[PDB]
Image (cartoon, grey):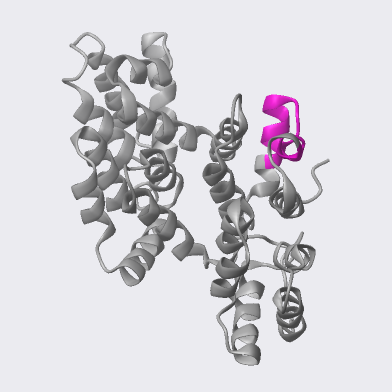
Amino acid sequence: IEQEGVTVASSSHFNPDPDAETLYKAMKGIGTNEQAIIDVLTKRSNTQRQQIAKSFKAQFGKDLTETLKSELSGKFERLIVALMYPPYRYEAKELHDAMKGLGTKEGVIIEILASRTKNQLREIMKAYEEDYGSSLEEDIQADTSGYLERILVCLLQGSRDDVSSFVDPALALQDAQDLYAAGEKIRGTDEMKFITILCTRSATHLLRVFEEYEKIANKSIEDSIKSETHGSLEEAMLTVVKCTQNLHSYFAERLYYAMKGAGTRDGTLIRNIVSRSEIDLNLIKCHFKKMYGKTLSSMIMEDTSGDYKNALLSLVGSDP
């Protein structure tokens, strides 16, 4: 389970018992030692933490996550619980939460379905079904509509990483040609062609289309997108583009906008820090600095507070 909260490097040989004991000492009795919880959980890998849960259950008779949900509050709680989830159940849960409440958090569904590989998505899908009873595709279908649903359902189908990934240039020039044909037709009548190309072609193929399109039309693919669609479908198409050009830049941007301007978008902040933790958080950090001047942690230092603040900082790690 290498998808939340790594140490600094990858790991090995490990007695989980002492850590399970510190967590116990920290929550036992009157008053809670939040620093100990931070020092264990944000400095062990997802796998290590899963093993700490097991020692914890056998040594003391209670489930670690439920004790966590029970002892802690606010963002701090949401963050620490988020850390405890296995890599695929975590996204499944966020996906479920998006649809379980009042309104759909479309941003959440877009972010996950578009940023994951076919095989990651496969795992999420199976994790969803086992934990929640129903099919993820059907829930998406019953909870969204229009062309948003079609791109979403297609993004579920699987061929972003199922395709051969070496570029056919006669097909790549056909695609940009088609997209470019759309511009002289009325906005709305071509949206199905955009979806098909954006969701059935590979990333390497797509990069080529973007190059041909720019050669052909004098405008970027981001502009042609804004000219043919609006709203959430636009957000979905723009997302797929950004994830194709630079997946690490997309996340950096998702993180910036969680904190940009007035207020904070904590759910966005948590999901991205936690889930990219043991994949590419060190690259996102690099892209974040380069794109916005300030470091991620520097922005964390100003927009968040308390034990929640310090856990993020410990999670993010040395941000030079």
Reply above or below: 91 against 257: below
Q: Quadrant of the N terminus?
A: bottom right
- Is residue 88 covered in magenta? no
Dominant SS of magenta comes to helix
42 left or right of 134?
right
**For residue 290: magenta?**
yes
Please report the residue visible at 77 percent of the width from the left and 51 percent of the height from the top: 317
147, above or below 124, in the image: above
Seen at 70% across and 50% down, the residue is 312
- Where residue 131 appears, x then y in whole percent? 36, 70
Q: Nearer the viewer, residue 233 or 312?
A: 312
Establish if 182 lies above or below 70.
above
Near-viewer residue (94 or 159):
94
Rendered residue at 64%/89% (across/down): 60
Q: In which image quadrant can residue 301 be found?
A: top right
Quarter where residue 213 is shown: top left
Residue 284 in the image: x percent, y percent?
65, 41
Q: Which residue is nearer to you in this view: 236 or 258?
A: 258
Q: Residue furthest left?
A: 189
Task: Specify whether 37 is left or right of 156.
Answer: right
Q: Which residues are magenta?
A: 285-301
Residue 104 can be seen, yes or no? yes
Residue 156 at x, y = what percent? 30, 51
Residue furthest front in the image = 30
Q: Is residue 1 visible?
A: no
Please indicate whether residue 250 sits to the left or right of residue 44 in the image: left
Q: Which quarter of the rendered picture does the C terminus lie within?
A: top right
> Where in the figure is residue 83, as x and y percent of width and height?
60, 62
Lateral position of residue 158 relative to residue 84, left or right? left
Give above or below for 39 relative to 284.
below
